[PDB]
Length: 216
Ligand SMILES: [K+]
Image (cartoon, rainbow, N blue to C red; front, side, top):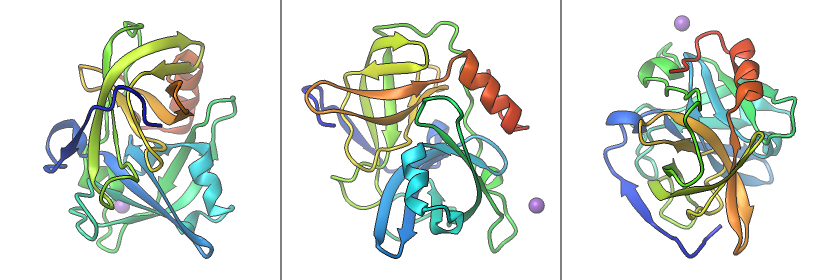
């Protein structure tokens, strides 16, 4: 949601640095198109929210992903279709999505370099972070970086003061070292925005379900 701190920048060179794995998501249901975000973390895997996955109504083939999308109809790495979904067993709004290779027999985690996950051993309140993804109040399929600070940490929940809008669901949260520390889910009008914090419980869950995930 939009907050007093509305500090966002557009990323035009999406395949440079840590931006490559940031992904644009489109869930093409027969009732309409749901837009969201996510991040590639393995050869065939990506992370996003449970509510974005629920928009498929149980059919994974309805979920399409375009890594490093620059703008409408400008996808440098093309798109990929989902084949399997696994939801987190805890309360956190988190889900794992596995994709099948594309027409050129390429893997989503091969055309782009998977993101590095943080151990979160030094993460604390008041540190500067960024939430990067695809906000729905901007031109279709454009990547934007939002800047702010962590304001709350408890268990597997985290809150911050930066702005986001519908479309940002599933956007990765990066620390200064450019490692992923959490996954954005949404917020509460005029109060805050929050994400799933990748603590010990969540980390164990990911390692048990993703063979090649990389933790720093
Ligand atoms: K292959």
